[PDB]
Amino acid sequence: ILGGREAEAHARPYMASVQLNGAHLCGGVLVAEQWVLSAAHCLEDAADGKVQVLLGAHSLSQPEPSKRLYDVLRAVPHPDSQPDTIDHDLLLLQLSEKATLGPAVRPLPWQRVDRDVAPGTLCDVAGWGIVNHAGRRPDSLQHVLLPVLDRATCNRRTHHDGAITERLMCAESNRRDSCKGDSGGPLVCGGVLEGVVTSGSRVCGNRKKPGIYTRVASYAAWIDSVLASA
Ligand SMILES: NC(=O)c1nn(CC(=O)N2[C@@H]3C[C@@H]3C[C@H]2C(=O)Nc2cccc(Br)n2)c2ccccc12
């Protein structure tokens, strides 16, 4: 997160760190007792390592009573995702067992009605992504509030030049932004999960290159089928 501040510890009990051999790769969001939602490109580099999900965390390194690193039984990238596109950029991770819930670990309700979040709406994004252009990794969870950017502006030649389909949404990126390592994390509006940070490479913090987030409501059939597949 660029331009953000350190989050209140455990104030976002849905927040997940998706890891490869104990290193943070991507954000994620606990959406059911046994399932974490993230972005499909997050496991690009994962084949020879172990994917895990850290729940209950504020610091990535320090001991906290609510922190628990779960193994992943199954990783289910969206079947229409492709390397080289950011369409269908969703991933569902089935934890080894149901997560232990409490005040610091709780699923986030997610948007099931397929209608646009209205523009200018202030949404929360949190993550352990990079905090400066040099690539510095924070140890603890950061967040920022970002206004939703209307799709027509996001589609202008100056911005993303018609790449923003109905299944994606944008947020402003003027200094305050999501960035590398925030990929897969949640964009929350009115206490409901609305978007998942995409996981393609991009500039961060440049107003003409808005952040792009996959609209969960657009994928409700897919999420529901996977979630039921246990
Ligand atoms: N939404 C964006 O702005 C964005 N998304 N990605 C993808 C990304 O982020 N990752 C891809 C999915 C894997 C793992 C992961 C990664 O490298 N993780 C990583 C690498 C170094 C430091 C930290 Br923290 N996380 C970017 C890459 C470059 C610049 C901006 C971004």
Image (tube, helix red, strand yellow):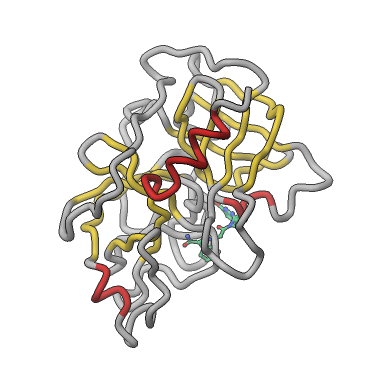
Percent across and percent down for residue 188 are 30, 42
Residue at image point 35% right, 30% down: 12
Residue 34 to residue 77: above or below:
above
Residue 136 to residue 139: above or below:
below
Residue at image point 48% right, 57% down: 198
User: Dividing the picture into quarters, in which one does residue 69 lie?
Assistant: top right
Residue at image point 36% right, 69% down: 205
User: Dividing the picture into quarters, in which one does residue 52 lie?
Assistant: top right
> Which residue is more in the foreground, 136 or 183?
183
For ligand 1, which image quadrant applies? bottom right
Q: Quadrant of the C terminus?
A: top right
Percent across and percent down for residue 66 are 48, 16
User: Dividing the picture into quarters, in which one does residue 58 lie?
Assistant: top left
Percent across and percent down for residue 202 are 49, 70
> Which residue is more in the foreground, 68 or 61?
68
Residue at image point 34% right, 69% down: 210
Residue 23 to residue 160: above or below:
above
Left or right: 109 with respect to 58?
Answer: left
